[PDB]
Image: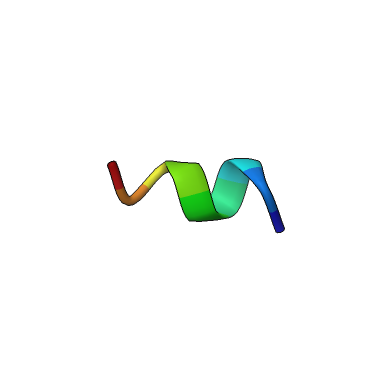
Amino acid sequence: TVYVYSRVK
């Protein structure tokens, strides 16, 4: 996903 991959940051 998008938001799921942005949470890492």
